[PDB]
Image (cartoon, coloured by chain):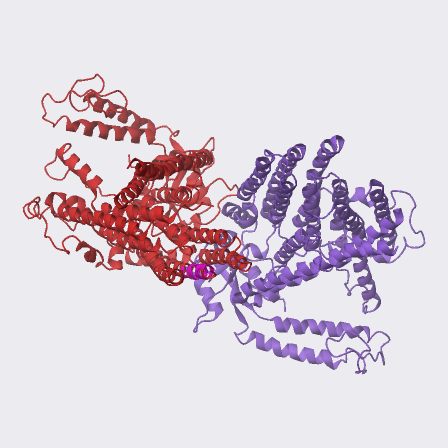
Chain colours: A purple, B red
C-alpha cells in the first residue's frame, strides 16, 4: 500500500489505456470498420460509404503513423465541437450527461487542492473545517449546474420540433363499464371534461403475443438465412435441442434450411391469426389510452390536473415519445404494479447480499493468489482483484434492467433511470459501506488502496476500452460475414446504441461517492478520481459525436436524480466523519458535524423548489408560447392527422 | 396515587361539573341571557326576542326545577338533530370537528376494554401483542373516518351554493414591470395564458393603515359613547395615560365626552385623507391579485397548474372565501414570509422552554403546598396543580395565534390550523415527553397520576365550564349596561364566536396522545380519557347547535392535519414501548416493535394517496358537473357582477 506500489499499478493501467488507444488507432483507420467507429455520421446522413466508395485504403497497407498525435489526436478533436452544435447533433440528454463528468472536475479539483494543501502538508479540527468547505463547494457547484441544465432544458423544449408527445397524455386506469368500450368511455370523458381541446385518442391494446410472434419470425428467418446462404442447395443439417432454436448440432432434428422453412411459414400463419384476433376482440384493449389534444397547453393542463374524485382512476400523465414507449409493459394491469414493485424490491435485497459474498471473496482470492505466489506479486494480486470485480459487475446493469422492466415502467427513459437508481444502492452497500462489514459468508467503508485499484481499472483502463468498441465490432463483423445477403447495405447491423445511462451514470456516482466520503479523511483517492472524470469526458464526447445514437430525448429529465445522488453522497460523507471524529475528538466537534447535514438538506430543498420544477412540470406560459408561434408559422396544420396514428402499437 | 385518592378527586371534579350544569340551567332560563345561550338561532333567524317579546319570565321567579332532567336534559336534546341537518344548520367544519370526539370513543373504547382484560386481570409479551392490536384498530378507524369525511366534503362541495372563491384564485408574486401596473400585468397574463375563461381580477392593495384608522374611530366612538351616555351633559372627567386611551383616571387630561370628541373627528379626517391616498397611488397596490374565472373548472385548472418557468412568480392558489381572508397579512412582502417563519420558529423554541419551567414548578408548588400543610391534603395538592396548569395554558392559544399571524398566512382557516399544529408540538414536549426531563431550571413521559388529574380538570370540569359561557356572558352584560344606546338591538354584542379549532382540537389531540402512549403500558388513563370524549361530544354538540357560529367554511379541510397527528401519536407510542420493552426484555421483542412503526407509516402513506387527494385537490370532473348544472338552472347569470367586487378590501 506504499506510494511505489500504487505508482507501479498506475503505470500498468496507464499503459493498458495507451495500448487500447494504439489498437483503436489501427482499427479506426481500417476502412471496413468505418460503420462501427463513425456510426453517428452515417445515421445523420453526413457520411456515405466506408471509404468514399467503400472499403479502400488506410488498412494494413499503411498501419498507423508512429508518433504521439497518431493515437491521441482524437482527443483534441473531440473537444472541438461547440456544445450548442452538439445539442443539435447528438441531443440534450447526451450533452448534459457529459456535464456530469465536468461537474466532477469542477467539484473535485478544488477540493483535491485543499486536501493536498491542508491535510498532507501538516500531516485536527482541520478535518472538520475541510468538511465544511468541501460541502459548501459541492453545493455551490450543484446549484449552479441545476440552474444551467434547467435553462438548457427550457430552451430546448421551446425550440424542439413537433413531437407527438407534446400534445398527448397517457390516461391510465379507465374505470370499466359494462355497456361502453374503453374508447367510448375515454372519448366521452374528454369531450365533457376537456371539451374545447380534446382532439383524438388511441386505446392501449395488448399486442404482446403478436409482437412476440413477429420477433420470432425475424429470428427464424435470420437464424437460417445464414444456413440458406452458407452455400445454398443442400446446406446445414444442424440439429439443436428443442427450446429456442439456438444451440446447433446438440439434439436430433437434422433436416435442412431456413430453420426448417415450415417454421417460418407456421409463424407467419400464427401471426395472421393473431392479427385478426387482437384487432377484433376488445379483450386485448387495456384500461388505458393515449389522449391527444389540440394544443400543448391543454395537454399540460390534463397532465398536471386531477380529473376525478377517485385518486386511482383516470390517471393522466404526459406521454412519452412513441419511440421511448416500452410497449410490453403497457399491457400490465395497474393492480399488479404494486406487487411487482415489492417483489423486485425484495429481490434487490437478496441480489445485494449474494454479491457481497463474491466481492469479499474477490478480495480474498487476491490474498489467496498472493499466498500461492514484492513489487510484481502485490501488483498483480491487486490488479487481478479489480479485474474480477469488473467482470462480476458488468453483469449487474442487465439484471437491474430486467428488474425494472418487471416493475412495469412504460418508457425506456424511466427504465434507465430506475436501473441507475438501483445501481446506486448496490454501490452504496456492496462497493462501499457494508461490503467487508458483511463479510464472514469499525471497518464499514472498506479501505483506500482497494478503491484506488478499482478506480484505475474500472475508470481508467475501462473507459479506454470503451473507445475500442469491441463487442459492437465483433457483432457487426459476424453479421456481415454470416447473415449478410445484401447488395450493399440492406443489412444494417451498424446499430451503435446509446450512452447507457443505466451503466455510465452509476459509475460516475460511485466515484462521486468515493471522492466525497474519503476526502475529509484521506486525500489519496482524489487524484485518481480526477483522471477518471477527465478521461471519461473526452472518451465519451468522442463517442457521443462519432458513435452513439440516442434512442430517446428526455431533455435532461434525469438531472434531478443525478443531483439527489450527489446530495446523498455529501450526507453520507458527513455522517462518516461524525463517526470518525465523533468518537471522542472534541465536545465542540459534535455540534459542527451535526449542522452540516442540516445545511445540506436545506440546500437540497431550496434546489428542489427553484430548479426542479423545470424538469417535473411544464409551465403553461411556455406551452402557450410554443402553440402560438407554431400556429403563426404553420397557420393550417392538421394535428389530427399527425397525432392519430402516432400511438398505435408498432406491430 | 391510590385508587381511593384518584376516586376522591374524580368525585370532586364530577361535582364541579354537575355544579356547572346547575348554574347553566339557572342562567339559560333567565330571559335576559337568551341571546348568549341561544345565539345561533338568533343568527339563523329562527329566534326572535329574549322571551317571545323580550325579557319576561323564567327567572328568579321560578328558579329551576329540582330533579335530574332539569340540569341534564339538554344532553339528550343535543343529540337529537340528525347530522345532515347539522351540516345545513352549522356547517361541515363543525360536524366533522364533532366527529373527532366520536373517533376517540371508537378508538379508545375497544382498546380500553382490551387493556382492562389483558393487562390488569393477569397483572410479558402481551404488552407487545396489545400494542399491535391497538395500532391496527386505531389505523382501521382512521381509514374509515378518512373515507367518510372525504365523501362528506365532496358531497358538500357539490351542493354548496355559489361562493366567490369557487371561481377565483390568488395570484401571488406578480413580477414588477416598469411600464405596467400590477392590474395591467395580471390582465395581460391571464388573457394570453388562460384566454377563454378569464373573467376579472382584483388587485391586492395595502389598506392596512386605513383599516387601522377605521378601527380606531370605532374604539374612540365606543370608548366614550359610554361617557356621553353615562349621564350626558357634563359627564366624566376621566384622564388616562397617553398611549391607547384605555386606563381611566391615570394621567392628567380631564376634559369631557366622546373621547374628547375632537379625537373622533380628527380620526375621521385622517380616514378621509388615507382614503384618497390609498386609492390614488399604485404604491399601495401589492404584487398580488385575485383572479376570477368564468368557470370553476378554469379556476381549478389555474390553481393546480404551473404558470411560468420561474417557480416563485405567478403563484396561483385557490382563494379563500372573502370572509376567511385575513386581510392584514395580504400586505406582507413574500420575501419577508420566509424570514418571518424562521423568526417565529425560533421563538417557538424559546416559548416551549419557558413554559417547561412553570409546569415543572406547577407540580413543584404542588409538593410545596403539601409540605406547608392524608386524603384531603393530597386531593387539593393535586387538583390545585392541575388548575395552575390550566391557568398557564389558557394563555397559549392566543400567543400561538399571534405567531401564526406574524408568519403571514392570509386565511383565518389556515391561521387556526397552524396554531393547532404548533400547540401539538408544545403538548408533545411540555405536557408530555420532555417536561420533567427538562426539569432542573428514564423518566421522559412523566407519570400517570399527574396526567389523570389533568384529564379530570381540563377535560371534565373544563368542558363543563364551556357550557356556562361566562366570558361571553360578562362581555354582553357589560356592553348592554354601559355602551348600550339602542332602542332594542342596534347593539349587537351577541357575537358567539366559533368552536375554536386552534384551542379545541389541540385538547383532543393531547388526550389522543396520552391515551395511545400509555395504553400498552398502563390501562389507567383510558377511562378518564373516554369520559372526556363523551362529555365533550355532548357539550360541543349543544354549543354547535345553540351558540357557536362558524366564521368560515373550509369543508373539513383540516382533516388531513388531524389524521396526521393521530398517526404521530401512534408512532410515538410504539417508540416508547421499544424503550420500555426494548431494554433487555426479549431478543424477539425487538423485531416486533420495529415493524410496528413501518406498518403505521405505510398505512399513513396509503391514506395520503387515497383519501387526502379529496382535501388538497379539486377534481375537474366535479368542477365541470357543478358548472353545467348551474348553467342549466340559472341559464343567464352575470358572474362578472358577482365576482368583481367580491375581493375588494372591506374598508
Q: Is residue A327 above or below residue A78?
A: below
Q: Is residue B15 above or below residue A204?
A: above
Is residue B132 shown in magenta? Answer: yes
- Residue B517: tell me if it is visible: yes
As drawn, the residue found furthest toward the top would be: B252
- Which picture quadrant has residue A551? bottom right
Q: Position of residue A49 (x, y in %)?
A: 82, 57
Q: Please tell me which residue lies in front, B257 or B427.
A: B427
**How many numbered circles are shown?**
0
Residues rendered magenta in the picture: B127-137
Is residue A323 shown in magenta? Answer: no
Q: Position of residue A349 (x, y in %)?
A: 63, 60
Q: Position of residue B368 (x, y in %)?
A: 33, 36
Helix, strand or loop for the magenta stretch, by majority: helix
Q: Quadrant of the C terminus of chain B?
A: top left
Q: Please tell me which residue lies in front, B584 or A392.
A: B584
Q: Is residue A279 above or below residue B455?
A: below
As drawn, the residue found furthest toward the front would be: B374
Q: Please tell me which residue lies in front, A537 or B124.
A: B124
Q: Position of residue A601 (x, y in %)?
A: 56, 42
Asked if residue B56 lies left or right of residue B473, the reply is left
Amino acid at each position: 500500500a506504499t506510494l511505489k506500489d500504487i505508482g507501479v499499478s498506475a503505470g500498468i493501467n496507464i499503459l493498458t489505456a495507451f495500448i487500447f488507444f494504439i489498437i483503436f488507432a489501427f482499427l479506426r483507420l481500417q476502412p471496413f470498420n468505418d460503420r462501427v467507429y463513425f456510426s453517428k455520421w452515417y445515421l445523420r446522413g453526413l457520411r456515405s460509404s466506408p471509404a468514399s466508395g467503400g472499403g479502400f485504403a488506410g488498412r494494413f497497407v499503411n498501419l498507423e503513423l508512429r508518433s504521439y498525435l497518431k493515437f491521441l489526436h482524437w482527443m483534441p478533436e473531440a473537444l472541438k465541437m461547440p456544445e450548442r452544435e452538439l445539442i443539435d447533433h447528438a441531443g440534450l440528454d447526451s450533452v448534459v450527461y457529459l456535464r456530469i463528468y465536468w461537474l466532477g472536475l469542477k467539484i473535485f479539483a478544488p477540493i483535491a487542492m485543499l486536501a493536498w494543501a491542508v491535510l498532507v502538508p501538516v500531516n485536527f479540527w482541520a478535518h472538520i473545517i475541510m468538511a465544511y468547505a468541501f460541502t459548501i463547494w459541492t453545493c455551490y457547484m450543484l446549484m449552479k449546474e441545476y440552474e444551467t441544465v434547467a435553462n438548457m432544458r427550457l430552451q430546448f423544449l421551446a425550440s424542439e420540433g413537433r413531437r407527438p408527445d407534446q400534445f398527448t397524455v397517457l390516461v391510465r386506469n379507465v374505470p370499466p363499464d359494462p355497456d361502453e368500450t374503453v374508447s367510448e368511455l375515454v372519448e366521452h370523458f374528454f369531450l365533457v371534461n376537456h371539451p374545447d381541446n380534446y382532439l383524438t385518442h388511441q386505446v392501449v391494446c395488448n399486442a404482446n403475443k403478436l409482437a412476440d410472434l413477429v420477433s420470432k419470425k425475424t429470428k427464424l428467418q435470420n437464424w437460417l438465412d445464414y444456413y440458406q446462404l452458407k452455400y445454398t442447395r443442400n446446406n446445414s443439417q444442424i440439429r439443436p435441442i428443442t427450446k429456442l432454436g439456438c444451440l446447433g448440432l446438440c439434439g436430433q432434428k437434422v433436416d435442412a434450411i431456413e430453420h426448417y422453412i415450415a417454421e417460418v411459414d407456421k409463424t407467419s400463419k400464427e401471426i395472421a391469426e393473431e392479427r385478426e384476433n387482437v384487432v377484433n376482440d376488445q379483450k386485448s384493449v387495456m384500461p388505458a389510452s393515449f389522449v391527444s389534444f389540440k394544443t400543448r397547453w391543454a395537454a399540460a393542463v390534463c397532465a398536471q390536473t386531477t380529473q376525478t374524485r377517485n385518486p386511482t382512476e383516470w390517471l393522466t400523465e404526459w406521454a412519452a415519445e412513441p419511440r421511448d414507449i416500452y410497449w410490453p409493459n403497457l399491457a400490465i394491469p395497474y393492480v399488479s404494479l404494486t406487487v411487482r414493485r415489492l417483489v423486485m424490491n425484495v429481490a434487490f435485497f437478496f441480489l445485494t447480499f449474494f454479491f457481497i459474498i463474491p466481492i469479499a471473496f474477490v478480495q480474498s482470492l487476491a490474498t489467496i493468489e498472493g499466498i500461492e505466489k514484492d513489487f510484481i506479486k502485490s501488483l498483480i494480486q491487486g490488479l487481478l482483484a479489480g479485474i474480477a470485480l469488473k467482470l462480476f459487475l458488468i453483469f449487474l446493469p442487465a439484471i437491474l434492467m430486467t428488474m425494472s422492466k418487471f416493475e412495469g415502467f412504460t418508457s425506456v427513459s424511466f427504465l434507465e433511470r430506475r436501473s441507475a437508481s438501483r445501481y446506486y444502492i448496490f454501490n452504496l452497500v456492496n462497493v462501499f459501506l457494508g461490503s467487508v462489514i458483511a463479510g464472514a459468508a469499525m471497518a464499514i467503508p472498506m479501505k483506500a488502496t482497494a478503491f484506488i485499484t478499482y478506480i484505475m481499472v474500472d475508470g481508467w483502463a475501462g473507459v479506454a476500452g470503451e473507445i475500442l468498441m469491441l463487442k459492437p465490432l465483433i457483432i457487426y463483423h459476424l453479421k456481415n460475414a454470416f447473415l449478410v445477403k445484401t447488395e450493399k447495405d440492406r443489412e444494417e447491423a451498424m446499430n451503435p446504441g446509446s450512452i447507457g445511462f443505466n451503466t455510465g451514470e452509476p459509475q460516475i456516482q460511485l466515484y462521486f461517492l468515493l471522492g466525497l466520503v474519503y476526502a475529509p479523511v484521506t486525500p489519496m483517492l482524489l487524484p485518481f478520481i480526477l483522471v477518471f472524470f477527465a478521461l471519461a469526458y473526452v472518451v465519451y464526447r468522442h463517442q457521443i459525436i462519432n458513435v452513439y445514437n440516442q434512442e430517446y430525448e428526455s431533455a435532461a429529465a434525469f438531472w434531478p436524480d443525478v443531483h439527489g445522488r450527489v446530495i446523498t453522497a455529501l450526507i453520507i460523507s458527513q455522517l462518516l466523519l461524525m463517526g470518525l471524529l465523533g468518537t471522542k475528538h472534541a465536545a465542540s466537534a459534535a455540534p459542527f458535524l451535526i449542522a452540516l447535514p442540516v445545511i445540506t438538506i436545506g440546500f437540497h430543498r431550496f434546489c428542489k423548489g427553484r430548479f426542479e420544477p423545470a424538469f417535473v412540470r411544464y409551465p403553461l406560459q411556455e406551452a402557450m408560447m410554443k402553440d402560438t408561434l407554431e400556429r403563426a408559422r404553420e397557420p393550417n396544420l392538421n394535428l389530427k392527422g399527425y397525432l392519430q396514428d402516432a400511438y398505435i402499437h408498432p406491430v
